[PDB]
Amino acid sequence: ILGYSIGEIGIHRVAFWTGAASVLFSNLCIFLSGTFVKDWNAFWGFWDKMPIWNGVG
Amino acid sequence: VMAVASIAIFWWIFYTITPAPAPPLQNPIYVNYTQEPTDYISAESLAAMNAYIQANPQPQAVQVLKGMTTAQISAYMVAQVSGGLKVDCSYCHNIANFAQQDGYPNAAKKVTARKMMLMSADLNQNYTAKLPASVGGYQITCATCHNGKAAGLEPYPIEIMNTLPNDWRLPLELDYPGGLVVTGRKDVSNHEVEQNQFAMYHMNVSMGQGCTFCHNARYFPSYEIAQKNHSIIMLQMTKHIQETYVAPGGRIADGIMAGKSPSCWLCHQGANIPPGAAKPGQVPAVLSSTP
Amino acid sequence: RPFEFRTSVVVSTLLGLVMALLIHFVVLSSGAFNWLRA
Amino acid sequence: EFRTSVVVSTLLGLVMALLIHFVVLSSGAFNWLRA
Amino acid sequence: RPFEFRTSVVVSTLLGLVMALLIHFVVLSSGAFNWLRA
Amino acid sequence: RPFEFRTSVVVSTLLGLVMALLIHFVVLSSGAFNWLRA
Amino acid sequence: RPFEFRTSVVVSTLLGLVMALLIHFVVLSSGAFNWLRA
Amino acid sequence: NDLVPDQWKPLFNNAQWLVHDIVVKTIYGGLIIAVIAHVLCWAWTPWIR
Amino acid sequence: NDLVPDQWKPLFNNAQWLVHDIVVKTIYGGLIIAVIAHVLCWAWTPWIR
Amino acid sequence: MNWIVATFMLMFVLVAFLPLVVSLAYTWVTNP
Ligand code: BCL
Ligand code: BCL
Ligand code: BCL
Ligand code: BCL
Ligand code: BCL
Ligand code: BCL
Ligand code: BCL
Ligand code: BCL
Ligand code: HEM
Ligand SMILES: CC(C)=CCC\C(C)=C/C=C\C(C)=C\C=C\C(C)=C\C=C\C=C(C)\C=C\C=C(C)\C=C\C1=C(C)C(=O)CCC1(C)C
């Protein structure tokens, strides 16, 4: 099933790492929202105007 | 210590090089918009104006603006009429006998201007007098809706509506005492909710503040913030503008404004209490809410 | 011995292709050449 | 470990040069590249 | 032995197909040829 | 042994089927043929 | 080896490429050179 | 082995030396071309002004 | 690991020493260029004023 | 004022990020 076996020592490392990473990214997001970003829709305004496709429309 | 020292050096650099923070524009009349360079108003026209003020005491044949003297009228015109549109002084006036239109003194503009004056007075009297205390006495004038531009203004620019679809417009064909409500209705699906959220984000971008400006996001149907009542009045006002002046029985027939819906952004322009809005006491009596 | 030759040719032909494609896209979208109805 | 020191040193130096170059450019006080 | 021939033909026939498809889609969507009601 | 025949026939019939389907979708959605109420 | 040589060349070519690309993009977007219809 | 000089013997292998040589030559050529291109971009329109 | 002097023998290996020499030389050159560039940026337009 | 303290607090957030990286690199090194 899915063609890969992680091993006995592998799964516990992955558990530890993912668990630890989730909360870190979360606290970063909240601290940032409070201090530097007023709304999140304006943040993505830059993507449309990427030179590669800014005039093809 | 290397890190904190580097951060200090960087901040000293920034403070030194950075150009100083800006003081807000202070103008005796408008809240945040000024007409200061009057080079756009030609100078030979300004000379001829002095003569008309000094020569006659009262203005011959004024249909509206009934309680004013030629000097007051001239000053008001140069301050707000030419100032709102940034037009030539002769843009809809002749050198003499400018009470009527003869010899195409840029005809078919003076009458549209007069109708704009009437419409502004009517809006001011019917809708901008609601919960006046604690909101201020600011009043709509030429600078509002025109922002220094004579014609060709756009009520929906491209910069706003980044997330919205470009075909979308504010839906003004609804009763709006509560017609947009969606919570718990059980006869509306996710499509109606999507239209609602489009309109709400538009109101969000128009107003400078965020989404908790008027909603108390724990319960959306609640009216505790009291900044919604103001929005109900403004919504009825925008619907009235569109229905009465933009398209009275079709844009072609008896329409002014060239079929441009008000859109809630051309007025406020990114802030509550829009900058073009005149401070209380700086608008003619006829044009103001209490005449 | 310090480098496998095939890794070099793989990365070379990937970088070159991506770079040609990106330049072609940018030049087309700039609208300064009157190419394909412009 | 010596290599940890050199890695963190270059990274910090590069980031710091880039940040200062950005701040000075965006301040608009030097008449550099049409200013 | 180092460079397997079949890897070359696989990547060749994939890149060629993708490239033909992309060019065909760009030319069709440019609207400059009057092809299929244009 | 160097090239399994069945891999060739599998990839051939998959590519052919996908290509026929894509072309028929594009032609139908172009709306230029008056086919099925158009 | 206090530093594997190949790590040095990898990081060098990556940093150089990124830096050339960034400078190019900044100079193009500044609009101060009259290059490609400016 | 043993093709690298004695002063750099503990650092460089044999194979690592020739690559290096290629890297140095390429860097010198690139610097010459960069200097020429800069002189040209200056003669066209100066950027400091 | 006997090319490094005795005072710094516990700390530095043999190979670490040469890379450390390269680092010191590069840092000195960079500092000289940085000082020249700041004198030039000052003569152009002073920042403190 | 506001921005000096803000940058200094962001430093602490990244320091909170730090230990997980040491865990990963320790595992990479000590498991040849
Ligand atoms: C005209 C002057 C401008 C100015 C704009 C800048 C800019 C722009 C920069 C600095 C930077 C520096 N400035 Mg200053 N500076 C000014 C005002 C000041 C004032 C003040 C008035 O009080 C002070 C105290 C400083 C102080 C400083 C130093 C802290 C710092 C560089 C020293 C360094 O780390 O070592 C020397 C430099 C190195 C980091 C080591 C050398 C590394 C080697 C040389 C790397 C070069 C390799 C090259 C990039 C690639 C070669 C090509 C290869 C082929 C790949 N500046 C005014 C505003 N300042 C520089 C910086 O580093 O910020 C950290 C930076 O770029
Ligand atoms: C409209 C509201 C927004 C929203 C706004 C927020 C906000 C605001 C935040 C999150 C945060 C979180 N949200 Mg969200 N979030 C929304 C929608 C979602 C959805 C979803 C499917 O839609 C999901 C899955 C999440 C998921 C999450 C994670 C990203 C994160 C979880 C907090 C946490 O891990 O750290 C929380 C960690 C702690 C505070 C626990 C500390 C516990 C201490 C150590 C233990 C004390 C001991 C205690 C007394 C018990 C003693 C034991 C004895 C038995 C009594 N959100 C909606 C869209 N979300 C939070 C986050 O970022 O984390 C910083 C946060 O800031
Ligand atoms: C019209 C002028 C436009 C412009 C448009 C383009 C476009 C568009 C392109 C370039 C590309 C290049 N341009 Mg130019 N370019 C301009 C101005 C410049 C300026 C400048 C004035 O400063 C410079 C320095 C350059 C420099 C360059 C090089 C960086 C690059 C190609 C160099 C080389 O030979 O390829 C390096 C060597 C090769 C590419 C090897 C080719 C390998 C084989 C031959 C590929 C065959 C492909 C084949 C079709 C696949 C099927 C084959 C099967 C066997 C059947 N251009 C102006 C703005 N330029 C090209 C690019 O880099 O793409 C790679 C690119 O497509
Ligand atoms: C009308 C002109 C349009 C345009 C439209 C197209 C379209 C559309 C296509 C190309 C394609 C190509 N164009 Mg052109 N192209 C234009 C302008 C250009 C310009 C330019 C002026 O700079 C250039 C350089 C090119 C260059 C190219 C090549 C990159 C490419 C094909 C080269 C080659 O022979 O194929 C390489 C070799 C082959 C493709 C081998 C073919 C293999 C066998 C014969 C395939 C048989 C398929 C068969 C039907 C399957 C069933 C067979 C079973 C046995 C039954 N075009 C203008 C804009 N161009 C073609 C592309 O690349 O797609 C592949 C593509 O379809
Ligand atoms: C009306 C004209 C429309 C158009 C509509 C279509 C449509 C629609 C199709 C094509 C398809 C094709 N078109 Mg055309 N096509 C047009 C213009 C073009 C132009 C052009 C002017 O440049 C070209 C070059 C082509 C070229 C092609 C070939 C790429 C392709 C089929 C070639 C071949 O014989 O099949 C290769 C060989 C075969 C397909 C083998 C068939 C295998 C067996 C016989 C399949 C039997 C299926 C059976 C029903 C299943 C049950 C059987 C059980 C035993 C019971 N078209 C215009 C726009 N074209 C066809 C496609 O590729 O789909 C495959 C496709 O369906
Ligand atoms: C027109 C003047 C513009 C400007 C535009 C640019 C642009 C654009 C670029 C630079 C780049 C550089 N500029 Mg300049 N630059 C300006 C002002 C300055 C000022 C200043 C007054 O203070 C300085 C100090 C610099 C300094 C520099 C260096 C940091 C850098 C290149 C140095 C070097 O030789 O490359 C180091 C050595 C090399 C790059 C080695 C090259 C390696 C080989 C030769 C690459 C070959 C690529 C080849 C095409 C791939 C295909 C090959 C296959 C074999 C086929 N510029 C003004 C604003 N400058 C260049 C940059 O760094 O990009 C990397 C860059 O592209
Ligand atoms: C703004 C005014 C001028 C301008 C001013 C300059 C100036 C000034 C310079 C350039 C430079 C260059 N410009 Mg320019 N340039 C302009 C417009 C263009 C246009 C175009 C679209 O018009 C193009 C295509 C270019 C392209 C280029 C390249 C020719 C060159 C940058 C080399 C470099 O960065 O790569 C370097 C890339 C890397 C460091 C890595 C290279 C990768 C190697 C070669 C690939 C083999 C890798 C090997 C297999 C190992 C694999 C390792 C893996 C990564 C792990 N310019 C405008 C017109 N441009 C710079 C240059 O020429 O100097 C050489 C230069 O100084
Ligand atoms: C605003 C007024 C002046 C200005 C004022 C100054 C002043 C003042 C200074 C500079 C400095 C520099 N400026 Mg400046 N500068 C200007 C405009 C430019 C322009 C251009 C677009 O116009 C360019 C390209 C530059 C570029 C530069 C570099 C030449 C230099 C910064 C070195 C540094 O940060 O790297 C340092 C990078 C790192 C610390 C790491 C280097 C990486 C090594 C070399 C790569 C090998 C790594 C090795 C393999 C190990 C790998 C480790 C891995 C990373 C882990 N300036 C304007 C015109 N600029 C500073 C400088 O020259 O001092 C030296 C300087 O003091
Ligand atoms: C002052 C109260 C006021 C004047 C005066 C005024 C005049 C005026 C003119 C002359 C035009 C037409 C210009 C042209 O060459 O056609 C015009 C057009 C529009 N106006 Fe107006 N206007 C005044 C006030 C206001 C206010 C407060 C609003 C806000 C709703 C407003 C709106 C508009 C709109 C819309 C147009 C049409 C713009 C176009 O693109 O067609 N005016 N006004
Ligand atoms: C949108 C636009 C404009 C895009 C532009 C780009 C275009 C249009 C095309 C680009 C590329 C092209 C032309 C791709 C074409 C691919 C083809 C035709 C593949 C072969 C099919 C032939 C096939 C599948 C024949 C397969 C063999 C089969 C079915 C045999 C099946 C069998 C199997 C396997 C058995 O057990 C035994 C029975 C039998 C032998 C019949």
Image: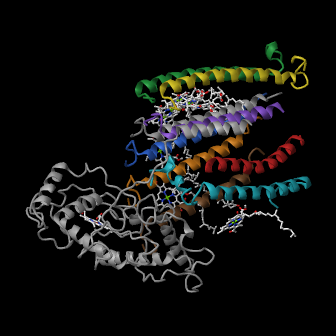
Chain colours: A cyan, C blue, D purple, E orange, F brown, H green, I yellow, J red
Image quadrant occupied by the N terminus of chain A? bottom right
| Residue at 50% in and 70% down | B198
Residue J17 left/right relative to B276: right
Q: Name the side, left or right, on which B166 lies relative to B256.
A: right
Place of residue B162 in the rendered image (x, y in percent of width and height, measured from the top left): 49, 60
Does residue H15 appear in this view? no
Q: Position of residue B266 (x, y in %)?
A: 38, 64
Q: Closer to the camera, C15 or F12?
A: C15
Furthest-top residue in view? H6
Rendered location of residue D11, percent (x, y): 70, 36
Looking at the image, residue I25 lies above or below residue C7: above
Q: Is residue I40 visible?
A: yes
Depth check: give the residue in front, A29 or A2: A29
The residue shown at (49%, 72%) is: B199
Residue B255 location, x and y as percent? 26, 73
Nearer to me, B11 or B107: B11
In this view, the residue in front, F37 or A42, is: A42
Q: Quadrant of residue B211?
A: bottom right
The image quadrant that residue B248 belongs to is: bottom left
Is H38 situated above or below B72? above
**Disc count in the image?**
0
Image quarter in which the C terminus of chain A is found: bottom left
